[PDB]
Amino acid sequence: DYAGNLTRPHWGGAASDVDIHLEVYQNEVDTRFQYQAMFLGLSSQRSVADRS
Amino acid sequence: DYAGNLTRPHWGGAASDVDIHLEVYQNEVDTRFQYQAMFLGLSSQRSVADRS
Image 1 (cartoon, chains in turn yellow, purple):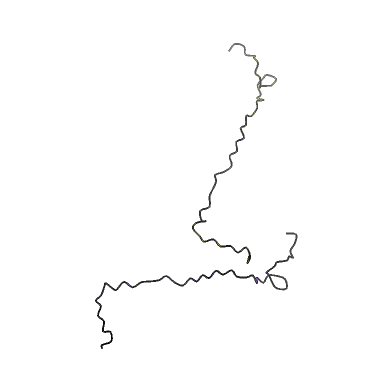
Image 2 (cartoon, each protein chain N blue to C red; image 1 turned 180 degrees about the vertical axis):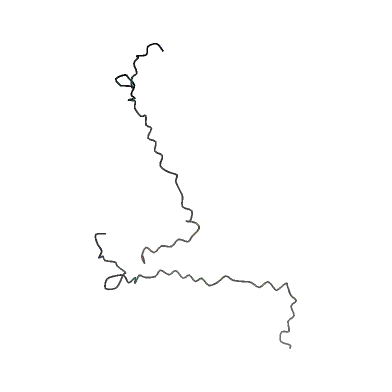
């Protein structure tokens, strides 16, 4: 193309070849897939908070 | 961690490790699974009662 030496704003380099852009970030974290316990209703519950 | 000698309340013995803890008991007795006779309509009933 014509004008093979042009101005690239966030491509700061000696020949304007190396990227220097900014990573846009929207506070996104991918951690894991959540799990819910399912033996709360399939077993009896007792408390020994005194006779430990 | 930093205390291999501790004060365990309901552990008796000279160097603890006796487990004299109380037993929590809620009046529960598991006995067996009951059975009901079915040979009532599967036979003929004759009552000798108080005669022979």
